Amino acid sequence: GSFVEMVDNLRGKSGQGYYVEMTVGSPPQTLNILVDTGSSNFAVGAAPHPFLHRYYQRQLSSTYRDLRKGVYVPYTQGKWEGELGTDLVSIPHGPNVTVRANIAAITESDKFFINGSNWEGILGLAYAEIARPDDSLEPFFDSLVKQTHVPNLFSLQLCGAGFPLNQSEVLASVGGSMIIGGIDHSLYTGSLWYTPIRREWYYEVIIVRVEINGQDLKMDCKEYNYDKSIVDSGTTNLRLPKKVFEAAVKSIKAASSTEKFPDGFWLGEQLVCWQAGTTPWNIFPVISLYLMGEVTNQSFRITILPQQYLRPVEDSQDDCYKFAISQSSTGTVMGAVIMEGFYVVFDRARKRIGFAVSACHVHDEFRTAAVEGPFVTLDMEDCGYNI
Ligand SMILES: CN1C(=N)N[C@](CCC2CCCCC2)(C[C@H]2CCC[C@@H](Nc3ccc4ccccc4n3)C2)C1=O
């Protein structure tokens, strides 16, 4: 129902990440931790780094336990390396519990920390199957559920401001909510619609249809989930498989063809600027992603606006944006810019993910983001990719 203690416990933005305050060790060491549904390790800065003004100091914690095991985590953009151990962990604006959890003390990294992000570690909220070095390293959420009476569910409301936030504003602003163990009804409007979690590794889902202003992209639905489709708060953009990206960008260009944008804009590399307040939202299409429903042959859709997929960036008094839709070779990624339109319920207990219109989504007087259903959709299991 209502979880006032956890409402408004996030800060940050799509491009630098959304983080929650946590404490580690005895006496407690306060750290800001990025909320990542696209990984499964609780990994924190444990050595000086130019982008960190604080880090976890294992030698100062009386409850620290050394697992005498290293961990090496390469990813696309970079890597993080560290030392495994356990310690007592709490979330000050969370449930009133303290858990004994695994912690990867980061001793080396490349393109991991973000300059000016105000976070010092990440909270891998996905399943043990993708935890590093392997699935025996119990993720934080699994420890939390196992050691307390917290229900096996969390929900995220990521609030994009709709305009740039400077260094001081982003520190003073409310970035959203992470509700641990429940659903807070003040964070959304309309109904919650649930899609099944296909498999418990990433929060994997199945997209069954895509529309650009009601026009069906008309691709074989397997293409939408090649090689997977995931909900990931640790990725900025809506990332699409190569072929889907090329078809979607062609359709988005055609719908907005009253204005021509350079190639670098469509490549998500270059900003586009309009005189203050004149952004022509109306020329850009809405994008609808239909997701497999909980009922056989039934789907629902989530609709996003250009206010979600045009990411506000400071240039001048102009209103500037980056195109926050990009190509992927590792399947669809519903990143923070998509999550900003919705209140997202990671219902681990019922192996499903819920979507509802966010009470904090950015819109205009003419259009709103939407979560609607049901729609008759056949052979949805065929939309899932295999091998
Ligand atoms: C997609 N994504 C994600 N959701 N989590 C990770 C790890 C994925 C797991 C998946 C299971 C297997 C192991 C790896 C880590 C990022 C967390 C968010 C901050 C980002 N930091 C970055 C990213 C890019 C950067 C580029 C330039 C400079 C800094 C940067 N900092 C790094 C990732 O790559």
Image: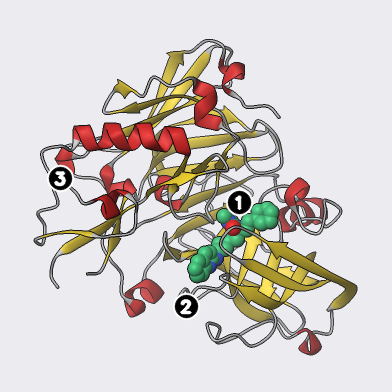
- Callout 2 amino acid: Asn
Which mark is in front, 3 or 2? 3
**Dot 2 surroundings within 10 Å: few (below 14), some, or many (20 or more)?**
few
Confirm or reject: label 2 Cβ below 8 Å from ligand 1.
Answer: yes
Residue at point 26%, 28% (across, down): 213
Q: Quarter of the image holding residue 292?
A: top right
Q: To which quarter of the image does residue 116 belong?
A: bottom left
At 77% across and 51% down in the image, what residue appears? 142
Disc 3 versus disc 1: nearer the observer: 3
Read off the residue under disc 3.
Answer: 260
- Whole-angstrom CA distance, mark 3 to mark 1, is 35 Å
Q: Height in image: 44 above or below 231? A: below
Closer to the chain start, of discs 3 and 1, is: 1
The numbered mark, 3 or 2, whose residue comes first in the sequence reads: 2
Q: Nearer the viewer, residue 169 or 8?
A: 169
Which residue is tagged 1?
38
Mark 1 CB lies closer than 8 A to ligand 1: yes
Q: Amino acid at mark 3?
A: Lys
Instruction: Point out the quarter of the image occupied by ligand 1.
Output: bottom right
* Tag 2 residue: 115
**Residue 120 placement, left or right of 316:** right
Label 2 SS: loop
